[PDB]
Length: 367
Ligand SMILES: [Zn+2]
Ligand SMILES: [Zn+2]
Image (tube, rainbow, N blue to C red; front, side, top):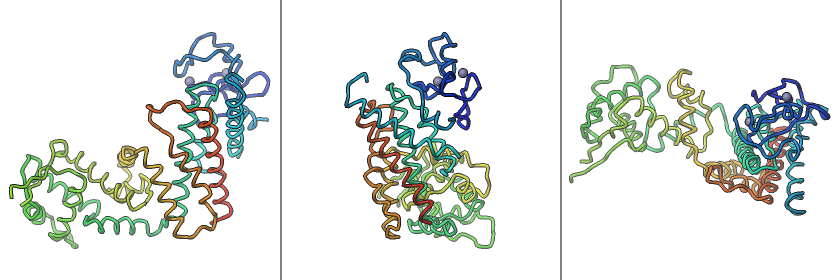
């Protein structure tokens, strides 16, 4: 069940061959060898316990996998099917040795999709979208300067009227804010700022009233405040935010959103480093970034890419991928998504191959 060995059957442990031990992908995303399918004599898949279509009889074998070793609904739909199958096969050849590890993981996910079933087709679409999105975020990093990245981030933060004082200093300030507001007190801007300023243990570049005001502004943008006015504006900490864990979570998330609006793709380890100074929060930041991902964020990313691509001119003519990327972003990731039609499946996979090929071409010929 390890994604790394896809050329071997999970059950029989032996590598796949073209005659007897034959790769057969099921609807659940697992590929088991034919001999084992015959040998099972049980309805479902031992790994997930999902029911099946019918036997080995109606299930085709993965050719896409076998390359690395050595007519139901009518003519139109099966033309679509054959084309799609061909696409997956063409992608699989990148798995022989070029692509990055996280990319090829999603490729492997794509290969294990059985295209003669609804489940497998849905999985194929999701894997397609994931591959597209990952390609976009890998094209953005090429046009993104890693050296001055932090500088740009903090610039974006300061431009919104917010401020980050550093990993320790910010913890201090936030715990002072929390101290004042944890019981439900309603303080105005100046009162909260004055309360926090005086309690700051002196370090050298001491935050002034304005800086702390900016940190408070950051907490206000994150919607931590119940804000009221009797005709001075009073701010209260919502019941769920009166813990340091929660409040800090919202704080971090807000800064991440600032990074997104400005178009900075930043890894969770880098976030843990910037915000906390250490690596302890990597999983925390991971959860934060994942929680922040809307299905509309793919399209957003495509647009951002187009912006950066408008800056440099276009040495690689990547705009040719624009109609392909827009199609990949237009498919519902939600479980509420209807199963794809045959034309949708074909167009999706075609889009995927065009895009991935484009990515490789860019990396090799333009840098
Ligand atoms: Zn087996
Ligand atoms: Zn399974």
